[PDB]
Image: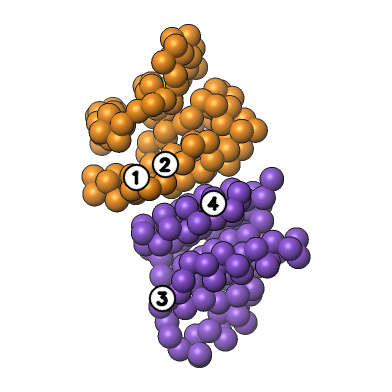
Chain colours: A purple, B orange
Amino acid sequence: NMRILLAEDDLHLGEGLLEALQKEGLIVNLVSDGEAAQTFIESGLYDIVVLDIGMPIKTGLEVLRNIRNRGIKVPIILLTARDGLEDRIKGLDLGADDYLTKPFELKELVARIKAISRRI
Amino acid sequence: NMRILLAEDDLHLGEGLLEALQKEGLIVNLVSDGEAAQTFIESGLYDIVVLDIGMPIKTGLEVLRNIRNRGIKVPIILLTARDGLEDRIKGLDLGADDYLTKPFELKELVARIKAISRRID
């Protein structure tokens, strides 16, 4: 069925989103560094991807760029603490489907994942 | 320190294993189906793998077979059962390095993980 990849180095945001999305019946996997995130996006196992811009090894923007250049279409939501409209546009222009800033309430991100889920 | 994979049909939310294992230096990644578990294992990014025997799609034994035949040598801990004695023997004969009764405690799992660490360094 449908699979969601969460790439967040923050453990507590990771587990919270895990519990919330698994409470909605969805299948959710969790990684915490860009190397793993990119590896498993390029594998085509995932239908939606949530990606933290601040990750070890490779950053969310490095990964977003890379996978898009490999021709993968998967929708990608970026998470970030960068509170600058300048960075938001640049993430959207790099290939992102949505863009959330921290702090956010989990129920918003859940709603955006479900809205994306309808168009796929 | 090292990356560990947990492939389990039952995810233990509300117990906070992530911080516990992370405080032991173990950076965790989570999956819940055999197909994704096999792909993660094949990536070679993990130093220890905890593999549930009864996963969807591909069971833990299928995954174990395929990745060992793929030449992947990562140490693996199987999550079996209580009367799964033949699952222990068979699982070990297929290349698994340890067992763990399915209703386990975080304490026993962490102990067996760090105890599997002494077969490399």
Cα distance between the residues tagged 4 and 3: 21 Å
Cα distance between the residues tagged 2 and 1: 6 Å
At label 4, which amino acid type do we have?
Lys
> Label 1 is found on which chain of the structure?
B
Label drawn at residue B15: 1
Label drawn at residue B23: none
Label 3 secondary element: loop
Q: From the viewer's side, name the closer residue of A19 and A45.
A: A19
Label drawn at residue A23: 4
Same chain for labels 2 and 4? Say yes or no.
Answer: no
Mark 2–mark 1 contact, CB under 8 Å?
yes
Task: Tell me the residue at 42%/46% (across/down).
Answer: B13
Q: For marks 4 and 3, give the one nearer the viewer.
A: 4
Mark 1–mark 3 contact, CB under 8 Å?
no
Residue B53 screen position, x and y as percent: 51, 25
**Of pointers 4 and 3, the one earlier in the residue sequence:** 4
Cα distance between the residues tagged 2 and 3: 25 Å
Residue B44 screen position, x and y as percent: 47, 41
Q: Quadrant of residue B67?
A: top right
Task: Tell me the residue at 46%/71% (across/down).
Answer: A105
Q: Residues within 10 Å of mark 1 (few under 14, many from 20)?
A: few
Task: Tell me the residue at 38%/36% (across/down).
Answer: B48
- Give the labeled residue for mark 2: B12
Residue B102 screen position, x and y as percent: 41, 25
* Observer able to see residue A72: no
At label 2, which amino acid type do we have?
His
Same chain for labels 2 and 1? Say yes or no.
Answer: yes
